[PDB]
Length: 7
Image 1: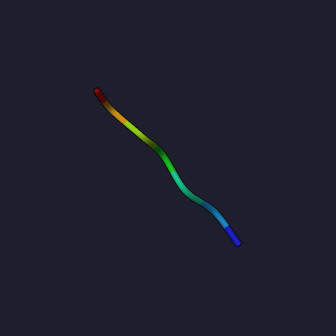
Image 2: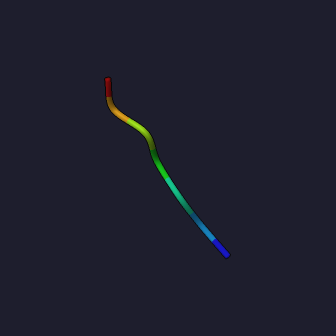
């Protein structure tokens, strides 16, 4: 699993 949250 890999995730990036760019607010």
